[PDB]
Every structure is written in C-alpha cells, then in structure tokens.
C-alpha cells in the first residue's frame, strides 16, 4: 500500500471484479470519491478488470481505464479509516 498527497491509499493489483450488488454500483470520474462526477452504473452480473485498488472516502475502490482513456473508480466495500475494518464485498474477485 501507498498513500499520495491527497491521502488516497492506492495499491497495484491486476484482477477482475463481477458486480453482485442488486441495484448495481455507481462509478465516478477523476478519483475514488463520492463527490466526483458520476461515470455510470455497473449493474449486477457485469464484470470489469481493474488495475489499481484505493481506500478513500470510507470505501475501498477499484480503478481501470476505459476504451476512451478515462479512468473510472468504483467502490467495492466499506472502509473505516480509523480502524481499517472493511465491510462485505459487493462482488466477486
């Protein structure tokens, strides 16, 4: 794990994620923060391959690049910054 200037915990990791959340997962642009503009919604059953994992804004995120070259961040589980406790995974890896 490594932390950048903004306090975003990131780590390299190459794996695939399949969304199992009933109502899908909302994706964001720019970074792993709920306040960033929405990039779409990944619905149940859909799978993506991420190249980096982040811990920020009370969640664990996975990121990847789209065909268009934009980086998209997706939350995958809750994260308590003060204790490090992580919640249920919203999909399979």
Image (cartoon, rainbow, N blue to C red):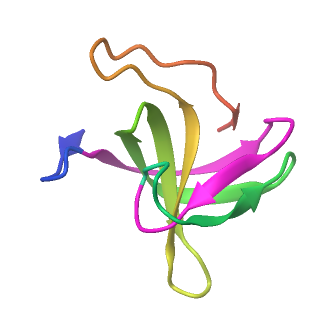
Left or right, 56 with respect to 86, comes to left
Image: magenta residue range: 8-31
Q: Is residue 55 above or below residue 67?
A: above
Left or right, 82 with respect to 6, comes to right
Residue nearest the observer in this picture, 58 or 3: 58
Magenta: main secondary structure equals: strand
Q: What is the x, y in percent for residue 59?
A: 47, 34
Q: What is the x, y in percent for residue 12?
A: 35, 51
Q: Name the residue located 31 percent from the left edge and 23 percent from the top edge.
A: 81
Q: Quadrant of the N terminus?
A: top left
Q: Name the residue located 82 percent from the left edge and 54 percent from the top edge.
A: 46
Magenta-drawn stretch contains 14: yes
Q: Is residue 76 above or below residue 5?
A: above
Q: Name the residue located 74 percent from the left edge and 58 percent from the top edge.
A: 41
Q: What is the x, y in percent for residue 64?
A: 52, 65
Left or right, 17 with respect to 3, comes to right
Magenta-drawn stretch contains 85: no
Q: What is the x, y in percent for residue 35?
A: 46, 53
Residue nearest the observer in this picture, 66 or 93: 66
Q: Quadrant of the C terminus?
A: top right
């Amino acid at each position: 794990w490594k932390q950048n200037k903004d306090g975003i915990w990131y780590k390299a990791e190459h794996a695939s994620f399949t969304v199992t959340a009933p109502e899908g997962i909302i994706t964001r642009y720019k970074g792993p923060w709920t306040g960033h503009p929405q990039a779409g919604v990944l619905q149940k059953g859909q799978t993506i391959k991420y190249d980096e994992v982040q811990k920020f804004d009370g969640h664990v995120w996975v990121s990847w690049e789209t065909f268009e070259g934009e980086t998209v961040y997706m939350p995958v589980r809750t994260w308590d910054a003060k204790t490090g406790k992580v919640g249920k995974l919203w999909g399979e890896i």
